[PDB]
Image (cartoon, rainbow, N blue to C red; front, side, top):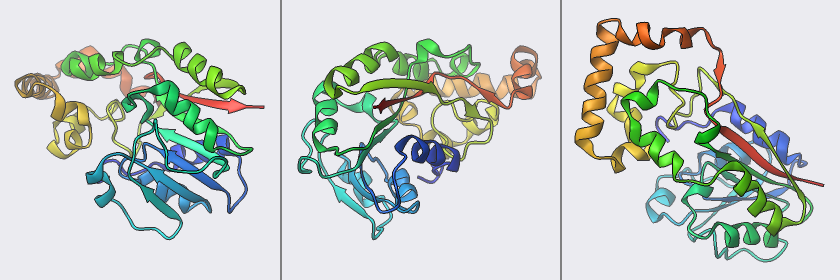
Length: 247
């Protein structure tokens, strides 16, 4: 959460889908560093942050309205009907038993809504990024199609599930994988790559060849020749989607 600074447009999107009054309680499943947990707590919500990573607990702001729980999504220590709403912001793809995690969200929730910021790379438009860093695409392609995700949630919630695109602005503060789509030079920075787990997990010689090719293309006008029209877009669809329950 140095380059993964929560973006207010994502927070406003989550807040709008939650549609909860001030003083409501939400569970944040797969809270990671807790940036969104704190960001939503600062909107006037109590947040129960659940994250298995013992590391990511320590790397987190102590906040009066955030309670931290170390555990897995498939077995929440939170009681039945203990929260008004539930969120998982770019986390569900890291869960090992997605169905049981969904059942768990339904178990803890009262009258509110489940808001998931997720993705399907199969729904994304052509992005230059993957021509330099194929591992990002390959890692994204491991996760389920949006329809399967919608269906699993819908089956374990018995509330209508809907989905909407979250088109990415060109100036997102939260530097997740495809967020620097209009700022190619940001990928050359070690710290930007440090905030995107796919880089550390990828074959390093591969990452390095991508860096060399990106650097050459940026310095000899090749990137502009091949991809420069992308600079005129204010936003792009890279398959990011909000899945959420309704009445």
